[PDB]
Image (cartoon, rainbow, N blue to C red; front, top):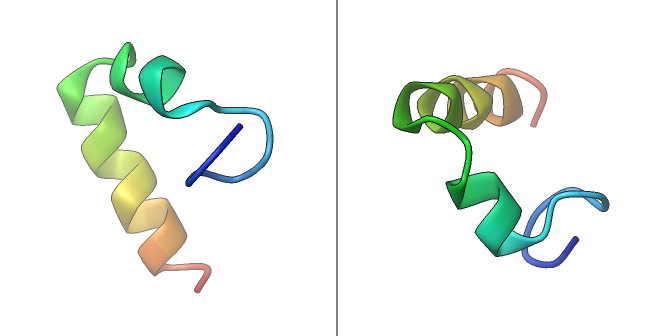
Length: 32
């Protein structure tokens, strides 16, 4: 992983559905 947690590499995060990406932005914004 890079520019993202530790596992998720940028490409793998963007291979997630756009609505999952959004929810993870809210998860990160509700944990930091």
